[PDB]
Length: 117
Length: 107
Image (cartoon, rainbow over all chains, first blue to last red; front, side):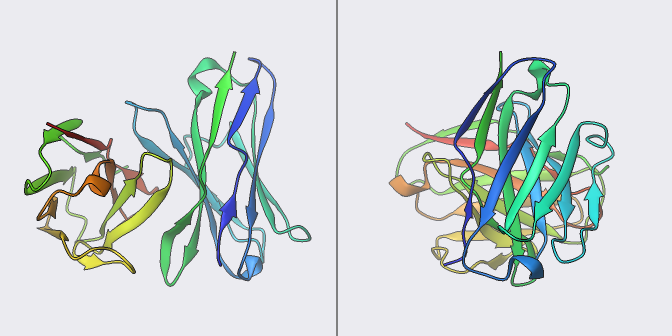
């Protein structure tokens, strides 16, 4: 049923940029918020921001304001996150999670491990 | 930001063992505490929400309690499938913040 699909890994070069994808499946993409979190092992889980696909409004952790840009493609039901000026500190696991049933992190993707060389 | 701290980063135990994971907030979060589990295959699931409400399809051996800034998760009988990493999250105020996680292992 409801499910989020992200590519499993991304090999990036420092200084460049990357756009992570999150494709929503069995539900009204337009009706729920999409969350993006970062997981550096041993360095905790971090909320990056939200985006409501039906309006485009976003909420950012002011800690990731100048780093991540959340966008969506209403046509393909895909949520996007672009990371700029990739640095080694950006190497982490990135999940997108959707809200559902009145809960903000109800469904999770399997994550995209980003390794910047 | 409200800092969440899971004191123990790694915990060892034997299957059948009764285990407890604690999580502390830097300030009262009025029971808006959620627990997530990340299985070895990379999947993440919502286990408990609002401190003690077990989520859909979660085994009864999982339980939560807490108030103020003190919260913990408890697994009555440690099962093989329970071997994973648990994270606590506060949903009291934005930005949402999570604890560092607790890795569960055998022995």
